Image 1: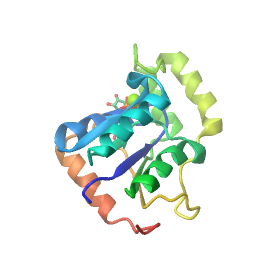
Image 2: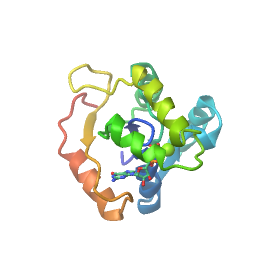
Image 3: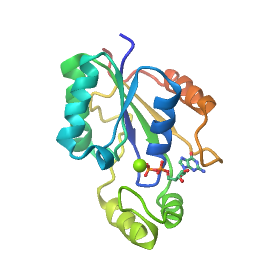
Length: 172
Ligand SMILES: Nc1nc2c(ncn2[C@@H]2O[C@H](COP(=O)(O)OP(=O)(O)O)[C@@H](O)[C@H]2O)c(=O)[nH]1
Ligand SMILES: [Mg+2]
């Protein structure tokens, strides 16, 4: 089938919303799941089921910061027999700190010097997926930041091409 669950993993300020907003703009048949606008994680799940029932692809724009957080979405993939691909945004804590410092307001409340302190607290819990330890993810792309702060349609195409060159970890 044409559809997938795309799990974004990355720190606050790493660029998850930038990528996901451009993706749904650029490519037919994609919906963005986001809790800071959606309401609750159950509401995210509810919307995800509705979209998968329509055979849509979904991009999970959440930090997806450890194995237990990712399991929600991997279980959903298994139930629907829909593959789970993952993009890990490889911005460092210092890069994200600098970006957060530049926010004046934000739906997450991770803003400015307050936001920097939040990020520091978060680092205790951030456990991105490893190629070895198998969670049921099909492929993992580790995506370097672009020099530019915006995401183009061309970047979206580059990303999907890079993802296609990633080895299959768990076969459908
Ligand atoms: N230089 C650079 N900036 C990015 C990139 N991706 C996002 N940004 C910038 O980093 C900031 C945080 O991005 P955001 O999408 O809000 O991060 P999120 O918290 O992970 O949703 C934004 O100002 C973006 O323009 C990237 O690949 N490279
Ligand atoms: Mg965001």
